[PDB]
């Protein structure tokens, strides 16, 4: 568990999420209670449950990104699930199953990077045994020519089931493989190096502790985001809607869910629910669920001034991504303040004209604006393309004017 | 083994009031020890006396059941009666009950294996001491003897179209209370001696609307009274590890002393009582959302207030709450 | 994986798809971004997501053909699924499952052909060491040419088992699905927007984690759909893309309208594309020794025949050409064995003889054409 | 393997079984001929050429399925008939290729056993000789005397391979539990006494399984489905077009990847439906072929209408086809020793009897000939034992005696005929 303070958490979210200060403060308090709980005695650690958060606001204002960056900041497993997925059926316990699997692959990538250098050394070390059968000189010669040289092209000799059983049959096939690579076979050094890295890294890593730490990641640092929870409130359909909340209840109150990776306890898992709440209201939720969501926070709708900030301020923003993508082709793209302002005004207009889709309108507008340059980027190499307010009004004003064309193209 | 009076006195450390319900759960748990002292013929003739709790929402029906099983070191599970109307099988109640007992006898084994297994570890070693065969079969003995199941909102499955599917849940739940054999991945489990506790508001229907075979399996009946403003004042302080005690200790982690005046605690309860009356009555759970809203400013600035003493008086409560409780439209969203 | 420029992709697509330049430029940008992401740093490779395409246009104009040729061009896994299939219901995750299975067979056959010639070369190579044991020169070449031409199976089995590893294949196939995967969702406009709307929008809600990126379990392993390219198509005459759920519109940034085909386009489809339907029929009759030639006036009346049937009853797109030709050539396709060594000329009169009688009767045109 | 028979040779062979419907015969002959035409093209043209599927139109009982059945039997091709309505409720459409691959593996197994039956007999009788003379000129004499003689009744003890575990499963797991049992048999021989008459046959079974390679037997069955496979889809006109229309068209949308070419997984490996020939049929009285989805119409290029059968066609079906019903009944009574003979006037009234029942109640096509014949021959087929040594001649009068009393009553015709 990290030891960051609420103010330090919010200041780090400001590098990604524009505005929405109240929502940042709500998630910061929940994350700070993770470390505060670790400092209590043994009696108070079990009594204190994570303070879940129910976000309220229109679509596309950053509710999910605040949760994504929060889990990425706290080094925690994260999963997003649609509340409407359980209306039709799939079991609600699948939320903890898919979250556990996401924690397994997470602790693996985190363990490989620490053990990558030793694994690469052992991989090429076994390749030198074939080149020179037993460092003297020849072994040191082939070792330097393997890293620097592209000689890897040299050839060197080193259950049918219904849709429900797709998960179990994959577990049975892994048992027969445990009870192939050892056999001497002919390969290419390019394809044999990548195959020897997998063999050496798997020997170095321990499946016992890596699987045990992933369970500790879901139980201690688990974060779950339930999108569009407002669509399961009471209104025929009201019995099935409230039936999903009743199945979600044992998750927030704490229970035991079995998974392929072991036994997972959802007591200390942090939950964050979001929804529009235009049709219904949070009071429409069942009383046992309202008590499990003590922290409430409203998020404000984004404005034209906010769209201007979203295009540039966040780390790796879309204008930054596109600036780096065309740089692969060798094109320097520059957006002037007068062009960024008209890109933002173009999205605000489409949302007012047809349907308000939130900040996601910036995605479809930008690709429409840059589709000509992106197609001709291989031919604009070595050039400096400047995106001003005129270039924006030439490729968009003709489109934003036609509302009928606005729904299809933007 | 605990006496009936000792159980109620222990439940008073968590649940405030509702004395009638505490006496009922004590009778069921005491008969567990009474049956163990009987002869071989009477141990199989005597069946646990199941409880049907009656009362409005948020009065503590579930907390009494959770603290009861935690007191007796017993497996516990809460299932919603409406879950089986649509689907998931009714036998799954015993399944999840079995899986919770495996983890419970596993954690208790991990604490013991923090010694002799550790000595040979610093010298897997627990697996050579704790046996999966001995552990798994011991978990089955824990479910058959000490098992405790809680069925919430059982009143919603009472009785033409939906009534057939509602009563069908009672028909499928019938073999569980009457005793049967349910197959689990951990082994064969018998539900004859498992304790069942049912609860419901019973405002739409009445317990007589249940199927007759089910009424005979619920001999103990108890009504729980609705909580009052005077009860809310008691819940904030009296119970061990109450929400104010937890928050007082959570803020001490940052180095901030929090003190609640007697006049502030009274007005905190008045706020929770007003929101339940203004919009919807969620019971004592309203104290959660109100406290977090009242303390969100202090919980955020707690890192900078280290070494200070913040006094929560009646004036501080009315400053952060009276504005919101007055607006009923906003109270449904924020509280 | 391929390093082709957007213009090289469009120029290659012109060998199959006629017209629809806007759609070709859209799919070229998507395929080019695959190579552009590979040149970025470690942080940007995960932040950059593939730009999915939402095609708009009537049926039979080539929306699917552009997607099929694109994946075949990039040596990428491909699958076509109908959006109405998921309206008890079949799980949506089967798209990634069927995509992975299709990629296993795709990479297996490609791996077999590489080994078919490399294992046989090494199989006969060990035979030469028994005949001419060295301590290749002319002695090995003398026996090598006499073994192929002159009058082994157990040596190919031992050599082919070393060249291809089943464990190496299944893992190489996953890299092809996660990185190079391409999925085509047809008639996505039919799942747009109370009860029927609940089941329609539910398909979009279940399709949402696929485009947003998630983890789907398959029998071959664990597959992540973050870097998979998705291409949706639809007529959008009943609904509009704005009627889609908002989370989905943000995942379909590239939009393109495809224009309806004309009579002049039908004439081009019969000849211009490589291995066109007329070229196939010329080669299929070539098996019997029969020369087939289509006059410029005959090709025009073939296209005019297909255009008229689409105008009279229902427009099935360019697929009408396949049914009209088979009806025209059914007599020649049956008599091809006896007409061996002859040359029949397909003129405008031969087309009008076997079609104008049928196209004139609309009642018979729905059954026969 | 792709048969080199010309389209006329295919129609010529189909006439030995199907009567009339020359239009449908030329359609199927064109399809099978393209199989060989595609095998002769370059590598580029083999993937671009797709099989020309056929859609047959006509009333029931005119020979649509028979033309399909005899076509596959002529080309030595896997075949399967599925009801389109089966997927409206449900079962997956991929099960079509699953059931098609299963019948092709059984087809290649029966054919491979009959072709390699001499090799498996060699190891079976040689294993018996290791028991008679355990290790010469004396060993050869035992082998020669056993084949000619009947020495198999003697008791001989031979070592033979000898789980017995049942796994209870819900109805959806009937497919996977049968495959888990096949892995336990895969992961020892026990000595027991037998008779050579019953041990030779029990040895041939063990030797047949060990001699054949599982991979070549399993891969050639795939190539037999991909290259030479055939599928028939009956009553496709019932899945055409608001309530059931979404489910009906949903069947076509699920059938679309089959005709467009895809990949369906099976327990015997991976099958590709690109070169699989599909044949759809239907009356098309309620709907018309144009009512199908556009993607499907293009995948059904060959179209042919089958003409309805007449009174003259019924007389031909009774006698002309090989092993026709009257021929089958003459040979069935031949077991009891009764020589049945059908006069030309008797056959003509049998056709006129069946024509009236279809005209009076419901028209079921040529299938009415079966219920009428058995009704006509019920007394003879019952007394066929005691009539041994007699020549029963079925004339026009005998037909009217047992049928004109029933055909006249329409209320009785729906129940009895
Ligand atoms: N305040 C913000 N700052 C930066 N990006 C934002 C903000 N709000 C929305 N976005 C953009 O919206 C996209 C995700 O929206 P999301 O948070 O899923 O919508 P919602 O909040 O309705 O769930 C991201 O790509 C992100 O770039
Ligand atoms: N008598 C009580 N004493 C203390 N806390 C209570 C009492 N009644 C309810 N609560 C609070 O309500 C929550 C439990 O409510 P629960 O028993 O689930 O509601 P219900 O009885 O309607 O099922 C607990 O968090 C607990 O703090
Ligand atoms: N632009 C085109 N060039 C060549 N053939 C085409 C073109 N458009 C459609 N076709 C023909 O139509 C068929 C594919 O149609 P398809 O793309 O599936 O329809 P849709 O685009 O409505 O999904 C192919 O057989 C192809 O020959
Ligand atoms: N033209 C024909 N020649 C010979 N027998 C026929 C002919 N038409 C029908 N039959 C007989 O009638 C039956 C027709 O059934 P079938 O062809 O399977 O029905 P359908 O074609 O309507 O699906 C077959 O058993 C066949 O023996
Ligand atoms: Mg338009």
Image (spheres, coloured by chain):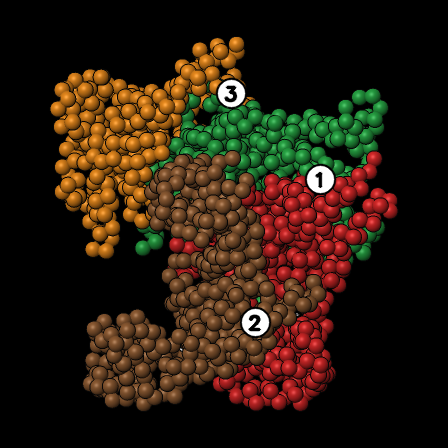
Chain colours: A green, B orange, C red, D brown
For label 1, the residue is A187
For label 3, the residue is B254
Q: Position of residue C324 (x, y in %)?
A: 59, 79
Quarter in which the C terminus of chain C is drawn: bottom right
Residue lying at 39% horizontally and 48% vertically, measured from the top left: D152
Q: Which quarter of the figure has residue A113?
A: top right
Residue lying at 42% horizontally and 65% vertically, measured from the top left: D82
Label 1 and label 3: CA atoms lie apart by 60 Å
Residue lying at 15% horizontally and 22% vertically, measured from the top left: B40
Q: Residue furthest right?
A: C138
Mark 3 and ligand 2: say if the CB distance to the nearest ligand atom is below 8 Å. Answer: no
For label 2, the residue is D32
Circles 3 and 2, Cβ within 8 Å, touching? The answer is no
For label 2, count other residues whose C-alpha is less than 10 Å away and answer few (under 14), some (14-19) or many (20+). many
Q: Is residue B221 above or below residue D123?
A: above
Pointers 1 and 3 within a single chain: no
**Residue A144 makes an appearance in the image:** yes
């Amino acid at each position: 568990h990290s030891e960051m303070t609420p103010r330090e958490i919010v200041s780090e979210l400001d590098k990604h999420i524009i505005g929405q200060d109240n929502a940042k403060r709500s998630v910061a308090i929940a994350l700070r209670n993770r470390w505060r709980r670790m400092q209590l005695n043994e009696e108070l650690r079990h009594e204190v449950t994570p303070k879940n958060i129910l976000m309220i606001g229109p679509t596309g204002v950053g509710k999910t990104e605040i949760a994504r960056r929060l889990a990425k900041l706290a080094n925690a497993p994260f999963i997003k699930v649609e509340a409407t997925k359980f209306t039709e059926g799939k079991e609600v316990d699948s939320i903890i199953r898919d979250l556990t699997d996401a924690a397994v692959k997470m602790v693996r990538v985190q363990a490989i990077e620490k053990n990558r250098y030793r694994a690469e050394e052992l991989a090429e070390e076994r390749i030198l045994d074939v080149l020179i059968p037993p460092p003297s000189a020849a072994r040191q010669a082939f070792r330097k020519k393997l890293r620097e040289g592209q000689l890897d092209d040299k050839e060197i000799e080193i259950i049918m089931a219904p849709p429900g059983m797709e998960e179990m049959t994959s577990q049975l096939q892994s048992m027969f493989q445990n009870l192939q690579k050892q056999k001497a076979r002919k390969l290419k050094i390019k394809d044999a190096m990548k195959l020897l890295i997998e063999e050496e890294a798997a020997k170095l890593v321990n499946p016992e502790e890596l699987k045990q730490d992933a369970i500790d990641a879901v139980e201690q640092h688990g974060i779950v985001f339930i999108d569009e929870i407002d669509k399961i409130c009471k209104r025929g359909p009201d019995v099935s809607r409230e039936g999903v909340q009743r199945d979600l209840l044992p998750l927030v109150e704490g229970c035991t869910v079995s998974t392929k990776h072991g036994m997972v306890k959802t007591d200390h898992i942090l939950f964050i629910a979001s929804g529009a709440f235009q049709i219904a209201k949070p009071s429409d939720l069942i009383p046992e669920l309202q008590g499990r969501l003590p922290i409430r926070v409203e998020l404000q709708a984004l404005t034209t001034s906010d769209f201007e900030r979203i295009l540039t301020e966040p780390n790796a923003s879309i204008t930054v991504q596109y600036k780096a993508l065309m740089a692969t082709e060798g094109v320097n793209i520059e957006f002037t303040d007068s062009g960024i302002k008209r890109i933002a005004e173009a999205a605000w207009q489409v949302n007012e004209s047809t349907e308000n889709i939130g900040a996601r309108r910036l995605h479809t507008v930008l690709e429409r604006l840059m589709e000509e340059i992106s197609y001709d980027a291989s031919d604009l190499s070595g050039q400096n393309i400047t995106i001003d307010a005129d270039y924006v009004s030439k490729h968009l004003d003709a489109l934003v004017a036609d509302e009928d064309l606005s729904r299809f193209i933007l």
